[PDB]
Each structure stands twice: as C-alpha cells, then as structure tokens.
Length: 33
Length: 31
Length: 31
Image (cartoon, rainbow over all chains, first blue to last red; front, side):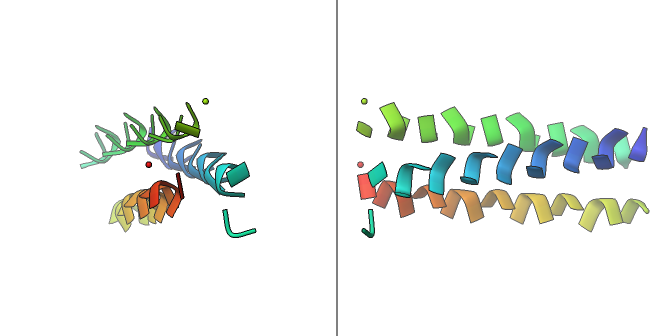
C-alpha cells in the first residue's frame, strides 16, 4: 500500500507538471511576446 | 503515519483540483 | 522509506506552493 501511495504521488506530480504545461499554454496565448 | 501521509496526498489532490478550477476562472477572464 | 516518502510529499507541497506562485505570474498578465 506504501509503494500504491508513492506511485499516487508520482499521478500527482506528473497532474501538476499537465497543469503547469496549461498555465505556461495560457501565458504563451496571452504575454511577454 | 502512512495512512497521515495518504490522507496529505489525497489534500494535495483536492489543492490541485482548487488550482485547476483558478486556472480554468482565468481561462474563462481571457472567454 | 517512510521518512523518503515524507520528504516526496514535502517535493509536492513545496511544487504546489511553484504552481501557485506560475498562477499568481498569470493573474498578474490577465485579472
């Protein structure tokens, strides 16, 4: 159940690295150039 | 302690699904 | 292993608090 949890954390980090790669889509639709 | 850590991880999932539902307010500002 | 697991979850809390500081860069473009 511990290593189910370790590889839930490795779902989360790779959800976060989708969200970051939406955020950095919106910044690059809208910003610096 | 694992069953504290799982129940931090399943908080971090329910921060990520806050942050996505902020990002998807900003995407629907921009609309 | 438990205290490797605690210190992945505190990489994750401290990613979440990077994403919030991308989102609050996006808010300071958009609203």
